[PDB]
Image (cartoon, rainbow, N blue to C red; front, side, top):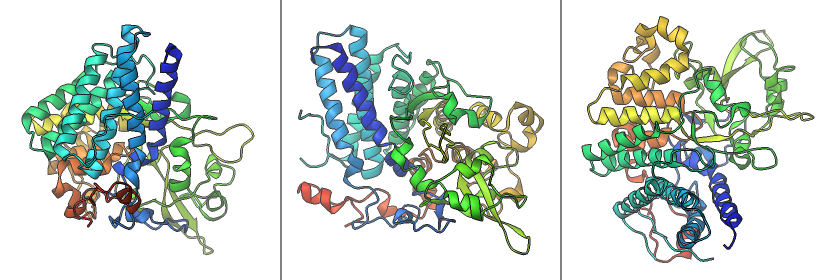
Length: 478
């Protein structure tokens, strides 16, 4: 640590460690809710992935072992904090920026741990005994958020890019953390006010909605667009999205696309871009959801999912199921299959708006603007402006669509439900739905998952327990 380049390299390494946990962030934040649970349509064994939608994880089958391997990241962050605080070799602005990032990343990891495991060890040392109560975990998260925001100050520039932690990333996390303490830990209105203000502060950065289309948010060719507050950089010869687990958990086999399935007209995917897809599906979006997720002309529908069909020997074309479609990757010259090299968004501007909407509702304030900014982008201004009475908030009520729809309610069921619905539509495959329902509490968890109220946290595996005799099993999983 005599050369400023060693700080740059170590910081880059911290961000690479976080990137390795992309897949775990997805798993922790999404598949225990209501999106998945059908058998893979292509016939794959789900190989234990089903224990997430079925909420059958337990002390023998934990879903994710060893706290998602987050503690060895925390150890390295703790080292960066100490070395950066001590050093005299950096400019004040450089030193502060690194501290803003390191404190923010530490809080971010601990906030996954709080929501997922509850009471956890507060490890604040580095190397190169028992848990603290959830309340004390949250106090540490808040302390690190304060340290982070104070270090960044008024510098909301993306000094190291949108794929590195920044002041707006800390404000997003702050909003999430104060919503959680407000709603889950009796904080009430004063915490909702802090949260609201944090989400408002995100707007100080150069952020806004990508309006051209929903698809352009995620495209390989439009990375680090203005919607990205914090996004995980993946790329050729650097890292595959989710370390390969997107392709190998959510994507259909090429042979099914080429030989077995057809489109809605009864025609083959041979000769089309969809013939390039090749992966393995162990988590299957519910087949019924494809027709109960989105109103007509919401472009998020066919950007997020594609319906596949089969044409029988009698010529009859029948709906077979949906395939995961949001992340399209790229086709490398010379290749025969798609490469899943998209960046993985963590915080997007639509997330700011919808969580701002949440904080507002919790305070009794009007969320209309935020909800409708997101909807207008989804339908496009032309269609939105022509169909406000049908699909603008608070008018998205169609009785037929909402009948036999276990995933969502008409707008007239209330603003909280409307924001849950909006987030569901907006954030498929982005790791949000389980955390959304968990934030609002058991009534919503129970509507939108098969979880049991005594088992809302995650169990701890035996390998982890027997390594640290001070640890007890998660309450409810004994």
